[PDB]
Image (tube, coloured by chain):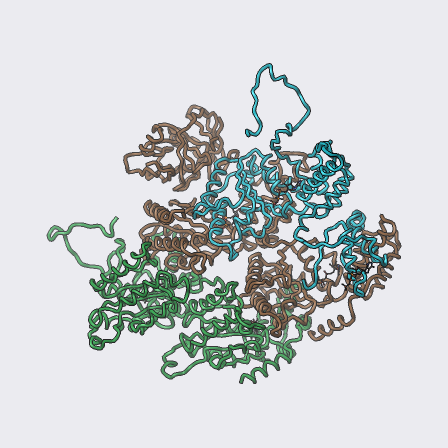
Chain colours: A cyan, B brown, C green
Amino acid sequence: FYLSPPFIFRKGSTHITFSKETQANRKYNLPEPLSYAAVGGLDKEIESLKSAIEIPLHQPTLFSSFGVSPPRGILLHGPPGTGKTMLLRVVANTSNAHVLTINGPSIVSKYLGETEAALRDIFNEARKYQPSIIFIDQIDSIAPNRANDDSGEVESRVVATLLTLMDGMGAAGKVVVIAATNRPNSVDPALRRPGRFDQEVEIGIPDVDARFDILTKQFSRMSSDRHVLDSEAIKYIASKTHGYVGADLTALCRESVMKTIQRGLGTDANIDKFSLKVTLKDVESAMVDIRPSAMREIFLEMPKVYWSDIGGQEELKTKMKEMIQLPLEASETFARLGISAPKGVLLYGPPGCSKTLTAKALATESGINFLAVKGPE
Amino acid sequence: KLPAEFITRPHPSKDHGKETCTAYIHPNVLSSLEINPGSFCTVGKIGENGILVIARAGDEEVHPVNVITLSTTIRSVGNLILGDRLELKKAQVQPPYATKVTVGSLQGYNILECMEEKVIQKLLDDSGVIMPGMIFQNLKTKAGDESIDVVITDASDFYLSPPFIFRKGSTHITFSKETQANRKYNLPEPLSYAAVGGLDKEIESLKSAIEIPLHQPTLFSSFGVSPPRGILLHGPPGTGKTMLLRVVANTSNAHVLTINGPSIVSKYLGETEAALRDIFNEARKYQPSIIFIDQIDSIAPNRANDDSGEVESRVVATLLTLMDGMGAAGKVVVIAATNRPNSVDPALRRPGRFDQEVEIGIPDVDARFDILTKQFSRMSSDRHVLDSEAIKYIASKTHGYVGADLTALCRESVMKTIQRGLGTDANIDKFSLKVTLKDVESAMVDIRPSAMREIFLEMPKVYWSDIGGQEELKTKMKEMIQLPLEASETFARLGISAPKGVLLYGPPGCSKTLTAKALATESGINFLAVKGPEIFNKYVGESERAIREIFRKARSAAPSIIFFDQIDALSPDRDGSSTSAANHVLTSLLNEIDGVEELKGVVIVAATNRPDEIDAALLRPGRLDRHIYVGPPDVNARLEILKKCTKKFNTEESGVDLHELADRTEGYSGAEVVLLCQEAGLAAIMEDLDVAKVELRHFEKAFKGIARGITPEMLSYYEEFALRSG
Amino acid sequence: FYLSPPFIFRKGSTHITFSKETQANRKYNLPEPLSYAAVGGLDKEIESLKSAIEIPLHQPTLFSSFGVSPPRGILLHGPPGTGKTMLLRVVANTSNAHVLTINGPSIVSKYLGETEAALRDIFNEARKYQPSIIFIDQIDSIAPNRANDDSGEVESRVVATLLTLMDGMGAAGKVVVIAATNRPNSVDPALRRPGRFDQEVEIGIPDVDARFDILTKQFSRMSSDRHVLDSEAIKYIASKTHGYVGADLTALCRESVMKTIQRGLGTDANIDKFSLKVTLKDVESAMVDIRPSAMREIFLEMPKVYWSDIGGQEELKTKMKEMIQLPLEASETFARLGISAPKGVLLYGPPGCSKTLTAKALATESGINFLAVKGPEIFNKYVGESERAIREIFRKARSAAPSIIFFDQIDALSPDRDGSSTSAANHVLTSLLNEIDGVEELKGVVIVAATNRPDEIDAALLRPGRLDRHIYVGPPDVNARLEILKKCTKKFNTEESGVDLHELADRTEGYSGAEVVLLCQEAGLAAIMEDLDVAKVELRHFEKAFKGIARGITPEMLSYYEEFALRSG
Ligand SMILES: Nc1ncnc2c1ncn2[C@@H]1O[C@H](COP(=O)(O)OP(=O)(O)OP(=O)(O)O)[C@@H](O)[C@H]1O
Ligand SMILES: Nc1ncnc2c1ncn2[C@@H]1O[C@H](COP(=O)(O)OP(=O)(O)OP(=O)(O)O)[C@@H](O)[C@H]1O
Ligand SMILES: Nc1ncnc2c1ncn2[C@@H]1O[C@H](COP(=O)(O)OP(=O)(O)OP(=O)(O)O)[C@@H](O)[C@H]1O
Ligand SMILES: Nc1ncnc2c1ncn2[C@@H]1O[C@H](COP(=O)(O)OP(=O)(O)OP(=O)(O)O)[C@@H](O)[C@H]1O
Ligand SMILES: Nc1ncnc2c1ncn2[C@@H]1O[C@H](COP(=O)(O)OP(=O)(O)OP(=O)(O)O)[C@@H](O)[C@H]1O
Ligand SMILES: Nc1ncnc2c1ncn2[C@@H]1O[C@H](COP(=O)(O)OP(=O)(O)OP(=O)(O)O)[C@@H](O)[C@H]1O
């Protein structure tokens, strides 16, 4: 209890000693504030969001002189697990301004007027203190499209009161609202307006270099002595991860840690778990063990067959390998030549020769997410 | 007897240079607030740290306890307009004397009444404190039946504006001209008629329908007709209804009550009507009152649907009864604004109550130009360099940009200017930079119109130079798209509209979709892409709603281009084998294209692979007028495609002339040439890993590997259909 | 805070003089009495209602010994805004008797017994206090049909007790109750079953005649001076906007007054409005700008079109005019002579033959009101919403003379394709058949339908009451094509170009109006593009635009239409 215990100071009994450590001791498991360096691969979006939040919040004289109203709300949309919530958390921690944790549908209650009274109280509290930020998560559910036949009445009322609070007779004062959702289409079109939600950022799936940056940031956050790795090894791991996101990378790293712990336990009995180290083959094993988030909804498995299993002509193997692996293994040559992959093959011939076995071999030793669909399915 | 909120009313006595900066307060309130009559008392409009440091004691019980009388001159700094809520704060701090102050005339004239023989007795002989800035009526001070207004701007030596104590001998008055108050400290300002542009024909009607029922109710009623009481404003969201309501509230000398929010309803059964009754009684009792009800659709839902079951239905019933209860004796006007005109209950929309309905449409080129010019005039002159011609050109470029999108465009242009200055001038002051046309174009590229927000289309940018095919199709598309928009005066003079019909039929994969992508990239106009079977839905009638919504979005997003890719998917319903959904979708499409309501500006483009499967109803004139053969590319087109694809490759190093190869690929198509080039590049990649050129052997191998898909039978059928069409 | 300031009067200490007219000063804000003269036009309905209400309200001793069911109601109903409330007020004021009644917004009570005891006490007082007229407004709101599940709640016992209680004090005794409602078919059929509502007097919207009379009456009522009094102007404004109800007329008068006020202020810089006078310009501006509730709830209006803008086979126009004007102008000739008009025409033909344009012109000329309805539009996701929507659009929005319903594509409703049972299309077709087989003359609905593929129409829909009139709607002839070419070439300079506009029409023999318009548009666009603005068209432009037209009307569909017409007979 009491989180971290306190202590009593004395003039001559402390015996202050100086140590070289930025962070506090980890034995107290105290929360660590987030910094902008934690998020990687999104430099342009981070800079744009930071500017669009800081400028309206601080020194609004620039906008007052120009006669243009400062932006009011910012909407963040993208695939789940991309890092929008962590971005909101880090921008809340870094900015020294009032925040209001309107997490979700906690505003609506069984009472008829409570669902609007709570929002009015929140907006009044935000307006009372000039530096204030509003962080809305899953705005689609609380404020859905009114045109839909399933919208209802209380949802329409809450949408109307949100619209009135954001824009109306009572103009907002130097307050910014941040909304995060995974389905921007479900958001009411009235909310997505230049007067309310002009600033829209589409946080897409990270690409290869963004994934490498995220992995490097995670490894830098980890202690240097905990794991030994090279920059080329991290780049190779990032290249192997195709459909991975920040959540997928975190899950991969955690699974690698667990695999390292279990390998140490197996190799040495009653050994210290903190003395183990993470190697490249361990990360590869964790990667092959775990599954990407996008492939979770796909449920199909086949026995593992290798490239050596297919007995036949090598021309098909060479052509399909040059179609598949070349754009990913060496993309600089394609970029220089300005040519893309053909992206298409048709296998026509006598039944049972090489088609389904080739598909299985690709699904096994392709290193890429595989999707199988049937004709009449 | 301790009300939470205090309302305000103007002083009954006219301004005469005395009793200014005094707010009468009921003795009961002063005793409860332990504030003596002589002190500095601050009032604010629910927060915002509003300050007025004025305190006075009311006389007997004639002054209502809830209301506080505020002078017109002192009410200008707080922007309160006849009914703004007021909060009492007993804490105060004695301010020091002011050693510097300036006076600025509101009018364009400068240096007026320099002697100040009688002016000094007004703003200098008064014992009460004077804010750094307000608006003075000054009554009449200049000969020639003209009244001047003075607005003090600067004053030096938690609160919104620090009040300064003045004295006649404290310092010297530096009279000058600085228009309104300085912007070094934030200060609310009124919105005038010049703020709203492009709505003159509607603003005059609104002015009349506000002034006549308020200023002269009985004078108008003398003829024998009840004066109008309800005004309804409806239109697309973000058009300027809220600004119009704010302007008519600020410029009017009548009480205003804000009941736009759904806060009128309460959990208690009786309160949702008691609050409305109290508000209407307060509006009627004081006499000159204006009522604004935004989002009336949520407050008063339609009774036709099952959504408005009990509570909102009884709210509408009570509102209707209380609206019909009042007579023509009082001077009260009710203003209702909503995004959906059809969501209002038909009971409210009646000639006896809501006859005066004003529709606000999407601004045209002239209205957009007027709005842009007014916004630039409001913006500081030294902060902008664009002239009238640039503003007109920008307005012409903007098609579906409503005033909200125009304001967003201006803000984004300012942000782009700031970013460019920071990047180029190595952290120079942001205030020194000025907006230019390049920043405006960059902001236009960055910002999409609000009407296209619901449509997500991530498409690669392809220009007309990339398509090296036949120039006849490009010329026809340009003459159909850009020509009517560029010069509509000639079309109006000649009395001919736009054909707005394209039927792209030909070999698959040659050029139909590429023209759609090319048009979307290099048209500068809103582009809508609709797939063939993507509109079908499992439920009955949901495809109807989807197509109606798509057409409504296209209509509301200015003239635009609709690309119906593979229109033949849902067309053929010659018998009962096809489901009724396809026939209903086809009928709805025909009705939306021509039907009964004419389509102006929007262009329908259809690309198909089987023109015969399309029903003759869509083939009639007025739907898909223009027909393009768009066959296989010619020798020149194929040579251009080969040159474009090989431009990255080293032609001179290899020695290929790009002519023998072009002659060899006579029977191929547009996509087959690209596939052959890709195969040659892949072979060059495999031959030596890294390479910067392609040799003739790779081209020969690719040509051997290419399988022709343009069968002569398909070309014969297409040419037979073409000759049948004629 | 009084209706009028009180005073003190004496005999010899004050002077008494008599002058002015009957009407009192308007500065007192006092109301004015309402008489039967205050209402014009409806009067034909009023004559029937005053007679029927009056025989019971006056001497009802005639049916004393008869013992038949006593007449205690009229059941007034009609289109919304028809002015029933002013008729009720007039009949209440002129009766100079007790008018004890209450409407309420479907007034109920939370207590189980009080919600009925209130009505019982009201009826007991009415029996004791014997009011001449009792007003029951909005019967559908307070007592709708029992067919709907949610409609029968609460009101069932109320209406049952009302029915079983109103059958009292027979022979002698007036106790006449007036039932006024907006929806005629929403009333409970069991409520209409007894014979006291056998008359079912329904008041229609003013039209054709008496409109100028009521306009003059309302103008005189508002002010006998400072206004224009011209018979020709009033007749013209009555003829214009034939679909305007009396409430729309009052709104027009109010907007004309507003326009006069605005013009006077803008002209004389806020002068007193007593001397201002009303002119025709402000009336026309008000008529343009009112947008009354008659065309509301639609938000869309058909484009303007005139007979000069369209030139076509005179036979079709003559047949359509005979179909529309003859029953619409009057109905007593049809009723007395027994003529049964088909009240329905089917427009089938090749696409682009301007059947929809013909319907638009018909609505613009005679109807002066259009109600555009689309087949697939009435379809709804819910099973029961489509039937309710089609019933609403068929009944509530229908007006007797003004409104005509036009079907863009009627062939998309009847065919259910491979539908066995429980289908939305089958349900809507059955509802339409039920709501169309019970109408013969009614109010001159004269529905009009257009189609492109007649072969799907004959699916349980073609009935002898609707196939009486068939219009071939053939392609335009050489004269019609020449007229279309001349109309489209009017903006061009024929004299400067020298084109005779004859050989072009002769060459285009198999074309129609749509193809002619398209080729003229293409020629104009080419002329604009080639040399900017030239204000003329040459023969080369027509030659260039000739290849743009895709064939035309192919003979196979023409033969199919001909054989379908022969089969129909
Ligand atoms: N750029 C990143 N760098 C490091 N870790 C990341 C990054 N993006 C995501 N993660 C990890 O993935 C987790 C999921 O991200 P976050 O909690 O921000 O949710 P989100 O992407 O907004 O999605 P949801 O829709 O589920 O709220 C983070 O807590 C973090 O551990
Ligand atoms: N070259 C080969 N090497 C190894 N096994 C083979 C080979 N050719 C066929 N087989 C075996 O025969 C089976 C039949 O081949 P496969 O399942 O790929 O069928 P297919 O070509 O897709 O034909 P179909 O779907 O028309 O029946 C394989 O699953 C495998 O067990
Ligand atoms: N005529 C106009 N001139 C200049 N700016 C305009 C105009 N109309 C709208 N805007 C801009 O759009 C913003 C939104 O307009 P406004 O606040 O008046 O709401 P509204 O049009 O009534 O819409 P909503 O129903 O969404 O509240 C304004 O704050 C202003 O920046
Ligand atoms: N004339 C051309 N110029 C440039 N590229 C071309 C040309 N013709 C074909 N291509 C290339 O070939 C591809 C195939 O053409 P595309 O699929 O766009 O044609 P389409 O006829 O509209 O399509 P589909 O018939 O499949 O609906 C194009 O995307 C482009 O990359
Ligand atoms: N004979 C008449 N002469 C003049 N005006 C008339 C006449 N009959 C009706 N009116 C007009 O009709 C209106 C009377 O409206 P009323 O209060 O009766 O409601 P309503 O709209 O007819 O009701 P509901 O829709 O419930 O039947 C007034 O505008 C009045 O001028
Ligand atoms: N006599 C004519 N005068 C003027 N224009 C005409 C004439 N005949 C045809 N047209 C033109 O051709 C068009 C054909 O009519 P419309 O487009 O309404 O289709 P429709 O013949 O009713 O066919 P569909 O069954 O496809 O609706 C008219 O709208 C008009 O532009």
Residue C492 visible in rendering: no
Side of B361 where B137 appears, left or right: left
Q: Nearer the viewer, residue B102 or B639?
A: B639
Q: In which quadrant will I find the C terminus of chain B?
A: bottom right
- Name which quarter of the figure residue B353 lies in: bottom left
Please say if C210 is above or below B654: below
Residue at 78% in and 66% down? B709
Q: Quadrant of the N terminus of chain B?
A: top left
Q: Is residue B698 left or right of residue B20?
A: right
Q: Residue at x 23, y 73 (%)?
A: C55
Note whether residue B548 is visible.
Answer: yes
Residue at the far top: name it.
A12
Residue farthest toward the front in the current orientation of the protein: A269
Left or right of residue B448, residue A287 in this image? right
Of C28 and B568, nearer the camera is B568
Does residue B549 sit above or below C349 in this rendering?
A: above
> Which percent across, then down, holds residue A30?
60, 31
In the image, is B634 to the left or to the right of C482?
right
The location of residue B670, given as percent across then percent down, is 77, 62
| Image point (73%, 36%), residue name | A265
Q: Is residue B665 above or below residue C494?
A: above
Question: Residue C352, position in %: x, y?
Answer: 59, 73
Q: Residue at x 56, y 65 (%)?
A: B592
Q: On the rendering, which quadrant does ligand 1 occupy?
A: top right
Marks counted in the figure total 0
Q: Which quarter of the picture shows residue B54?
A: top left
Q: Residue furthest left?
A: C12
Residue C445 spot, x, y in % from top left: 44, 74
